[PDB]
Image (spheres, coloured by chain):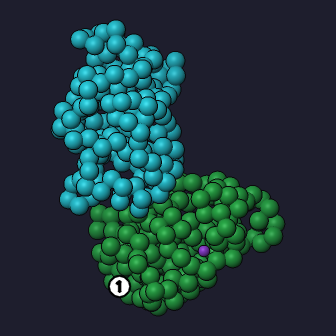
Chain colours: A cyan, B green
Amino acid sequence: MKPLYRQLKSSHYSSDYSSPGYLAAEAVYAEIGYELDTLLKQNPGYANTCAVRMSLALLKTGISFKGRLPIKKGAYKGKTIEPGAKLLADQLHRSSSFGKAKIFFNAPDAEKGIGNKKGVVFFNKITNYDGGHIDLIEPENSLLTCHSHCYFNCKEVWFWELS
Amino acid sequence: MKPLYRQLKSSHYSSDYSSPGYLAAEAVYAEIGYELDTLLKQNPGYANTCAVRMSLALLKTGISFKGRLPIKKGAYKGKTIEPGAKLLADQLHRSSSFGKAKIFFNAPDAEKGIGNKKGVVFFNKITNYDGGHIDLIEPENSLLTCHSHCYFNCKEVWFWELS
Ligand SMILES: [K+]
Ligand SMILES: [K+]
Ligand SMILES: [K+]
C-alpha cells in the first residue's frame, strides 16, 4: 500500500514540543516495550529517534519495510522497527510503496524540487548533527515545515512525494 | 539574481561553536580539497575563514564571483573561493546579482540602517581583529544576530538586504 500524507502524519510522533502530535522519546520507546535509558547504554545512537518514529508511523499505516528492532509490546508486538535513518531511507528508496527518492545536493534545488508537494524527507549528513533525519515535510505559509524539524544544512536531501 | 536568505544560510558553515550550522576550519578546507595547516604556512591570513565560508555558501546558491583559490574537490571543483573578506565584499559590491552595498561609517548608523532586515553583512576594519568579517545577519527576538559573529566595532559596515 501507499500511505496518505494526512494519515501518516496522524500516526507520526513529533519530537517538537509545540507540535499537536508531540511525544517524548522515552514514551515512544515505552510504547514498543523498551526503556530508553537501557537502549542508550547498548548503543548511544538510539538517542536519534527519527527513524524509530517514522518506522512506527509506517507500520501503523500498513507499510512494509525491513527492520532490526523487534517491538515487544502492543498491537505491533513481533513487528520490527528500523532505528537507523539512512537504513530506513534505503528501504523506502528500494520499495514499490515509495519508489526512488528524488535526491538534491543543495538547498535551492531541494526547496524547488519539493515545491508545493508534501511527503517524506530525509536529510543526509547534516552539519553538526549525528545520524541524519527522516521526517514528514509539507508547505506552510509559502515555506516548508517538517513534523519534527528540518535540517537543510546537510549534504543530501531525499524526497518522496505523498498524496 | 539575489539568493534567498534562508537558502544562503542553509548553505553556510558557521564558525560559532554554539551554532546548529557549525563546522570547524579544518573540515571547511577539507571539503574543497585543502589542508588548513599547509595553507596557514603559505599565508597566516587563512586563519580568518569567514570569506571561504561565505564563498562556499554563494557557490551552493549559484552566485558567481571572482576568486583566487581553485577548488580541488567536490561539486564545485574548478571554481574558485575568495579567502579574503574585503575582496569578496568588493565582488558582491560590483555584482549585478547583489548590487551596491549600503555602507555605514559607524555602529549606531549601521544598527539603524540594518534595523529589522536580514542579509549579508561585512564588517570592515574591526578593532582588535585582523582581516574583517563577512557573514549573514538577521533579527532574532528583535536583536540582530550573525550566523558566526557580529563585529560592529569597526570602521565600516556594508550591508546587502536579502529576502
Ligand atoms: K525537534
Ligand atoms: K526526531
Ligand atoms: K568563484
The residue drawn where x is 63% and y is 57% is: B74
Query: Which x, y percent locates residue B63?
Result: 50, 74
The residue drawn where x is 57% and y is 54% is: B23
Image side of residue B81 versus residue B104, left or right: right
The residue drawn where x is 31% and y is 36% is: A15
Q: Is mark 1 within 8 Å of ligand 3?
A: no
Q: Is residue B56 above or below residue A57?
A: below
Quadrant of the rendered structure where residue A26 is? top left
**Residue under mark 1: which chain is it in?**
B
The residue drawn where x is 54% and y is 68% is: B59
Mark 1 falls on what kind of element? helix
**Residue placed most toward the observer, B110 or B59:** B59
Image side of residue A93 versus residue B22, left or right: left
Query: Which x, y percent locates residue B117?
Result: 32, 76
Q: Is residue A110 above or below residue B91?
A: above
Quadrant location of the C terminus of chain B in the rendered image: bottom left
Image side of residue A70 versus residue B90, left or right: left
User: Farthest residue toward the front?
Assistant: A96
Query: Which x, y percent locates residue B137?
Result: 41, 71
Q: Identity of the amino acid at label 1?
A: Gly
Quadrant location of the N terminus of chain B in the rendered image: bottom left
**Residue placed most toward the observer, A58 or B157:** A58
Image side of residue A10 versus residue B46, left or right: left
Badge 1 is on which residue?
B113
